[PDB]
Image 1 (cartoon, rainbow, N blue to C red):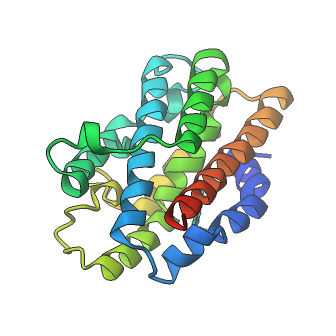
Image 2 (tube, protein in one colour):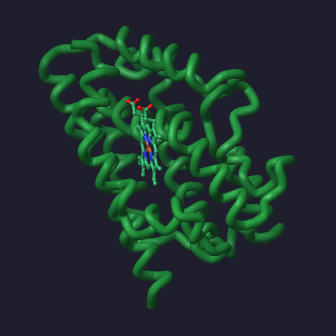
Length: 213
Ligand code: HEM
């Protein structure tokens, strides 16, 4: 069975759980505040920073290399612009770095540094979501918070080098399917994808509590 299918199957249950975290439930209903939106976007800034550091570290490693698409996919630059938008020109000392964010970053560095054959799980969990359901979330954010169609403050959700997210997702899946796969790697990759999802749920749990304190 192809890796792209194996990952979709292995994470469909946990995905349902992630959508129904209290934070995402509120987000999807259009009940996201600037305060809540800033917290989550600052946490993604740290997460994607770590993810992409490790991608760059492993760009030539054949257990990752076919998924090397910085121009199309990388989010760090977009997130910097968003941080300048939401937090102002001194954003680097204004943005929070929460413990649940630190925990996700830590696992990203473990994977990138010690288990790079699992990095695909982490890329899959973030980028394929961003190209799919992230575009729905963009539209809700825009409407909730009166964010302009010109895209300021939502650079994260914008892929100016990808014409068509569906076709690119199909390419990315096809290329995932060219990674050298053994039963051992496949099984652990799908497990790590479930972990990546849990790390995201734990962040959403944490942020909700911080908003409700
Ligand atoms: C309310 C929150 C969310 C909504 C409404 C949402 C919605 C979606 C939608 C509509 C799709 C496309 C499904 C399909 O094409 O069959 C999707 C795919 C995806 N979503 Fe999300 N999602 C949300 C949260 C998340 C979170 C928190 C993660 C990961 C952290 C994520 C990861 C993904 C991934 C990896 C895919 C690709 C599945 C695949 O094709 O293999 N989603 N999601």
